Image (cartoon, grey):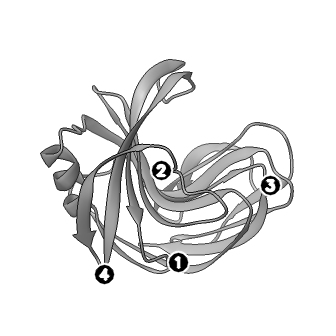
């Protein structure tokens, strides 16, 4: 299991972050594979992909995702200028991250309808330090743990709705958790 941080493994960018609570391990495997095992964790995010991402990447993911509590499985990344944290959520545990959020439309992509939302983080950690910034969400109605994500369909639908992205920073397939348990094994390409 590896030290929290970022870097490259077998061709792929990876990012592994946690809040120090303990209770989560992240491992990098061959090619685009990574595993996450957690038991009464704190907040964490880990996965593999690209640095920088692009606005027309077709991202393939495959494997197993077994959350017990609050967790997401998503295409996850950031833009700069404007600073945005974004999610194309393919599956989740006990909490739909769009709960209570204002719905800003729908997009159909890769075998499912997704609902689109914007939320705001106020004075929270980001890739550039503490900041207030928007998050964009596409939440898949039909949950899965393998598939293909045509990111352009999401980014274009977001732009159509007034949710603009800046320059891309990293772009990964990530398992996120918040004080939960579970296991995941995911291969990205």
Dot placed on the residue nearer the N-terminal end, 2 or 3: 3
Mark in the foreground, 2 or 3: 2
User: Marks 4/3: CA distance?
Assistant: 32 Å
Q: Residue at x 34, y 59 (%)?
A: 115
Residue that carries the numbered disc 3 in the rendered image: 24
- Whether tag 3 and tag 1 are in contact, CB under 8 A, the answer is no
Q: Residues within 10 Å of mark 4 (few under 14, many from 20)?
A: few
| Residue 142 coordinates in the image, percent (x, y) | 43, 77
The answer, for residue 10, to whether it is visible in the render is yes
Q: Nearer the viewer, mark 3 or mark 1?
A: 1
N-terminal-most mark, 3 or 1: 3
Real-space CA distance between mark 2 and mark 1, rounded to the nearest whole angstrom: 19 Å
Residue bearing the label numbered 4 = 111
Image: 82 above or below 116: above
Q: Which residue is mark 2?
A: 98
Q: Residues within 10 Å of mark 2 (few under 14, many from 20)?
A: some
């Amino acid at each position: 299991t590896i030290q929290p941080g970022t870097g490259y493994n077998n061709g792929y960018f990876y990012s592994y972050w946690n809040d120090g609570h303990g209770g989560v391990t992240y491992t990098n495997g061959p090619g685009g594979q990574f595993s996450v095992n957690w038991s009464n964790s704190g907040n964490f995010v880990g996965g593999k992909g690209w640095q920088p991402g692009t606005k027309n990447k077709v991202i393939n993911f495959s494997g197993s995702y077994n959350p017990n509590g609050n967790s997401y499985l998503s295409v996850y990344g950031w833009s700069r200028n404007p600073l945005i944290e974004y999610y194309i959520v393919e599956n989740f545990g006990t909490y739909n991250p769009s709960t209570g959020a204002t719905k800003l439309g729908e997009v159909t992509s890769d075998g499912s309808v997704y609902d689109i939302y914007r939320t705001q983080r106020v004075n929270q950690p980001s890739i550039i330090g503490t900041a207030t910034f928007y998050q964009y969400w596409s939440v898949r109605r039909n949950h899965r743990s393998s598939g293909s994500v045509n990111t352009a369909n999401h980014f274009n639908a977001w732009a159509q709705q007034g949710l603009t992205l800046g320059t891309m920073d990293y772009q990964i397939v990530a398992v996120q958790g918040y004080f939960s348990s579970g296991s995941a094994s995911i291969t990205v390409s």
